[PDB]
Amino acid sequence: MKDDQRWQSVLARDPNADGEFVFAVRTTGIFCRPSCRARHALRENVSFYANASEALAAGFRPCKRCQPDKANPRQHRLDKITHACRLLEQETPVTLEALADQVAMSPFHLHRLFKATTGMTPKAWQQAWRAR
DNA sequence: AAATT
DNA sequence: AATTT
DNA sequence: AAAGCGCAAGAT
DNA sequence: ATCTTGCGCTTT
Ligand SMILES: [Zn+2]
């Protein structure tokens, strides 16, 4: 596709576009993912690169808000829950804090993601395991 | 606070 | 220096 | 004592 | 502007 279509993805801050490409702003020398929450730049200052690597190669450093140099969190986050599920499969109660420490996530994110991935809270999951 | 104007 | 997210 | 929950407050 | 954390209160 052309860059104008890519541009519309950016103005739309469309997450579906993340990974597909990365845009760079010559006035800042920073590159971001299409869904970056940062105010947008003027079209004339933007350019696109198929991926971070190429961006770096071109002298642009990653944005500190969208971390466009790291791959899609998707899997990473999924790996987090799975591990938490296993740590909860024991009679002795595990607090969200001890759990968060273990999977290395702010208790807020862990709790939100867990209920999002499993469908219940870490607490319930441990109770369910005990149950059956 | 960090990006962009 | 001021705006914008 | 810890989980949950809505909202103020802090951070990016 | 948008998202995360801290708080006080009720429920587990
Ligand atoms: Zn960014």
Image: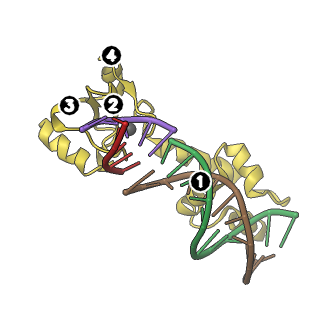
Chain colours: A yellow, B purple, C red, D green, E brown
Q: Position of residue A29 (x, y in %)?
A: 32, 24
Residue A88 seen from this side: no
Q: Which class describes the residues within 10 Å of circle 1: few (<14), some (14-19), or many (20+)?
A: few
The reply to whether dot 2 and dot 1 touch (C-beta < 8 Å) is no
The C terminus of chain A - image quarter:
bottom right
Query: What's under tag 1, amino acid-wise?
Result: His
- Are marks 3 and 1 in one subunit? yes
Q: Which class describes the residues within 10 Å of circle 2: few (<14), some (14-19), or many (20+)?
A: many
The reply to whether dot 4 and dot 3 touch (C-beta < 8 Å) is no
Residue annotated with mark 1:
A109
Q: Position of residue A13 (x, y in %)?
A: 29, 49
Disc on the earlier residue, 2 or 1: 2
Which chain does the numbered disc 1 sit on?
A: A
The structure residue drawn at horizontal position 29% and vertical position 17%, both measured from the top left corner, is A58
Q: Which class describes the residues within 10 Å of circle 4: few (<14), some (14-19), or many (20+)?
A: few
In the displayed structure, does residue A5 sit left or right of residue A10?
Answer: left
Label 3 to label 2, Cα distance in Å?
Answer: 11 Å
Disc on the earlier residue, 3 or 1: 3
